[PDB]
Length: 108
Image (cartoon, rainbow, N blue to C red; front, top):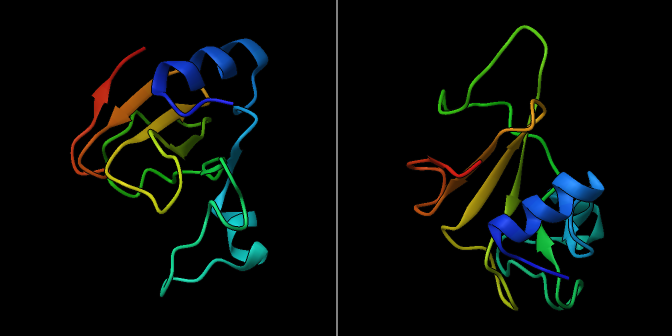
């Protein structure tokens, strides 16, 4: 269990998998996610949104003719998302934001 940027990176960089508490919007949606509520700790106690893919629809991540980008929530407990998010590239690049994708800072 963990919800910190470096914690997710260490966990993933070592076990190449997201912490035992990261489920993407994919499942969050079929699981029964609703905008007029933003559920999470209820249907997923101690869990966070992450594991999808980030089609760099912001021109804020390094691209290449053969690679992929994925996002994941950061610093969460029980409620909804926030402005803290982590971006991990298929090239093993680690990117982090704090204003909600607005700006981005690299960490590893």
